[PDB]
Image (tube, rainbow, N blue to C red; front, side):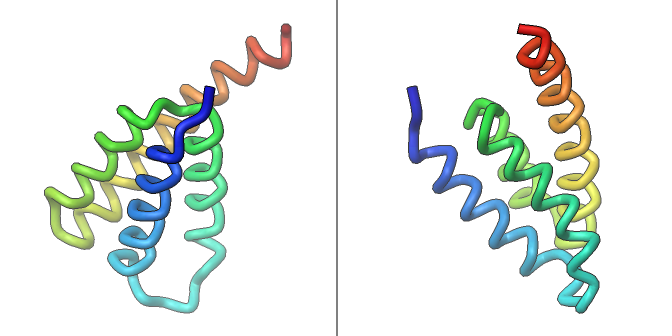
Amino acid sequence: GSKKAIKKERQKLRNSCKTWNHFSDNEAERVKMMEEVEKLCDRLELASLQCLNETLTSCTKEVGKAALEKQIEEINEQIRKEKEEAEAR
């Protein structure tokens, strides 16, 4: 039904993401990413969330940030696909 494992991973991924983002005051950029990460937590399986975490923990900060954003956007699209059906019924 619900697992806190995804929340733990989200807390790790989000925290790591901010620390390895750019340490800039541009929070708006991270806001969209955070909104998408929130969506990941809401419907994405933790297995996928873990995969993204591994990538950003397997790459440098810039690579991990770019890779994480690219992966998060792809996941967001997948969430949107689920949302579309969810909205349908």
